[PDB]
Image (tube, grey):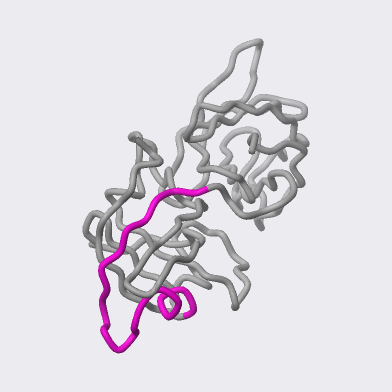
């Protein structure tokens, strides 16, 4: 049902390159991005399910793939708020709003995951974001005392949990198609950090 084609309208703005709700900065100024309505955003009951995903959008002039970096506040289902460069390729900007058909598509990237640890994170409370993923990340779990604890995905595109444990963290993430992948990131600090930081990933969802 995730591959299903979506129908809606699209507008444009230049607000997703910086300060987007999904905290995916920095976004290359020349990239094709988009803001997505709240309904479609939270797919499968998981908040920000499509955050960081890539959509293939088709307008009256053609198709293009966009990177979901922000939320489209009060937007209706199927509604998208594309960046100028993306909108211009599938439609006429002088039209202000265009009809579209889109669907989630494999991320046109290379490499493995990259994790972002939000400020204030530690072994007591942590928010961990997954970046550079081929498909949308549904669910993320970490291992503690031989058990896999499930982390709740938040609106700010980060998986949160408390009492993460000690030592390096063993995590496992599942995509929108049920594909699972395991990895291990360095230990979390003993006190909430002042600034967020990134940590390299060693895995990726299957093609």
Tell me: residue 102, above or below residue 35.
above
199 vs 39, nearest the viewer:
39
Quadrant where the C terminus lies? top right
181 relative position to 96: left or right: right
- In the rendered image, residue 60 lying in the magenta stretch gets the answer no
- Please state the horizontal and vertical placement of residue 3, each as a whole percent of the image: 40, 41
The number of callouts visible is 0
Residue furthest front in the image: 61
Tell me: residue 74, above or below residue 128.
below
- In the rendered image, residue 97 lying in the magenta stretch gets the answer yes
Residue located at (43% from left, 80% from top): 88
Quadrant where the N terminus lies? top left
109 vs 139, nearest the viewer:
109
Residue located at (30% from left, 69% from top): 10
Q: Which range is magenta?
A: 85-105
Residue furthest bottom in the image: 94
66 relative position to 8: left or right: right
């Amino acid at each position: 049902a995730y591959d299903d084609l979506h129908e809606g309208y699209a507008t444009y703005t230049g607000s997703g390159y910086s300060g987007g709700a999904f905290l995916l900065d920095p976004i290359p100024s020349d990239m094709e991005i988009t803001a997505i309505n709240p309904a479609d955003l939270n797919y499968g009951g998981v908040k920000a399910a499509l955050a960081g995903s890539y959509l293939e959008v088709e307008g009256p002039k053609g198709k293009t793939t966009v990177y979901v970096t922000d939320l489209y506040p009060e937007g209706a289902r199927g509604a998208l708020d594309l960046s100028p460069n993306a909108f211009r390729k599938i439609g006429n900007m002088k039209d202000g709003k265009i009809n579209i058909k889109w669907r989630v598509v494999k991320a046109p990237i290379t490499g493995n995951f990259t994790y972002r640890i939000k400020e204030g994170s530690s072994r007591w409370w942590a928010a961990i974001q997954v970046r550079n993923h081929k498909y949308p990340v549904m669910k993320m779990e970490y291992e503690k005392d031989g058990k896999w604890i499930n982390m709740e995905k938040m609106d700010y595109n980060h998986f949160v949990s408390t009492n993460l444990g000690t030592g390096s963290l063993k995590v496992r993430m599942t995509d929108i198609r049920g594909k699972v992948v395991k990895d291990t990131i360095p230990k979390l600090p003993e006190s909430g950090t002042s600034k967020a930081y990134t940590v390299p990933g060693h895995v990726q969802f299957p093609e």
